[PDB]
Amino acid sequence: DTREILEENNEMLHMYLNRLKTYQYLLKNEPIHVYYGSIDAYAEGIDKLLKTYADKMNLTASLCHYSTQADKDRLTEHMDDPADVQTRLDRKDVYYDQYGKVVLIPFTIETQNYVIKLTSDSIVTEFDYLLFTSLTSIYDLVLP
Amino acid sequence: TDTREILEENNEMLHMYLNRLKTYQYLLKNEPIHVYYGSIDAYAEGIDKLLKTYADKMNLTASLCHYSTQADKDRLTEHMDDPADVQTRLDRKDVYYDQYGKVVLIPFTIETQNYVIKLTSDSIVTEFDYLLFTSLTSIYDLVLP
Amino acid sequence: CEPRAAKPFKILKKRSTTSVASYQVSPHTARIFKENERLIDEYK
Amino acid sequence: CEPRAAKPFKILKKRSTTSVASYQVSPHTARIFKENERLIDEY
Image (tube, rainbow over all chains, first blue to last red; front, side):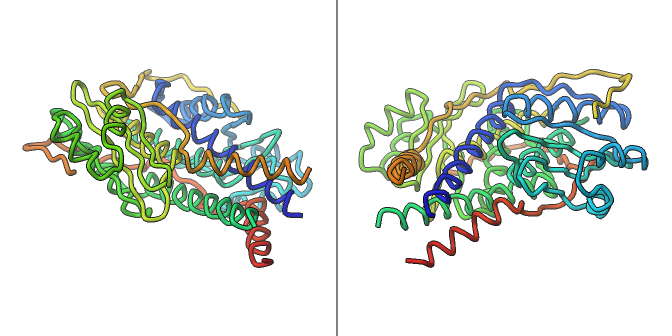
């Protein structure tokens, strides 16, 4: 039925208009707190910025270490196929859980590996990839 | 009837703004921002070049237009069926959209100086573009020392 | 998944010297939202 | 409409200290696009 598809289109447009509204509002009104001087300071500043944005959008964002095998195993525990999830991430691909609830985005600060974890009770998509990775770029551009 | 068309409109909207957002992110990732400062005119120049960098790759035109002198205002609003109305909106500092999705005019102020960010397109420009293009003006300010 | 650091310095960056007309939905997309919802509600 | 300055000072800034996995569509939106086009075809 075209009804269902239509509700899906409508939901997509509303949701990403709202999330884009939030992104733009924050770039305009929220002071960016810049942490620098080491990988861990940078990582903290990125984590806080992602959080500031996810908090106002009905989804959670986190910056997860993805350096040591211990880090990798921690991340992938709660997934159906951890070895496979890990291969994808190692290969540097975005990983989308099929049901639309989790995006995992391999991310690098200087020479340290992380994964930006995005979850949502409704839906996350490539639009969220684009918005959240844009912010990591803005963070880098705002450094001295 | 009214359903096939609306479906094409939804589909077009989702493709277009996915594409424009792909471009925006790609440029934030790979294109250096060139930051002009030292005066109101340098600042306005840098904002104009940044908007242009992005619009150039997106199938729409962006400009930063003076909106100080009546001459500036008339230049802007003579392209419109109701100039007095367009002008009153802009003067009162509100965004102006045409009914047809081809023009967005966004009052913008640098220190004491008034401008209007003009966005036009042969396909479509909407509030999404307002959001992207105003986002960029915010990134410009944040990048200043 | 919550990296914290001792940090050498703290800074605050803001968008300040400028202001912009605030958000409003376009007529174009307002029409699309209205038609969507009126059609969704018409199958149901 | 093209404001230019008489003697600007310029600063080139670049996203460098970080990098990210590159773009890939989610399955969810891939499905929506496919179903749209298959329905649009169906009139």
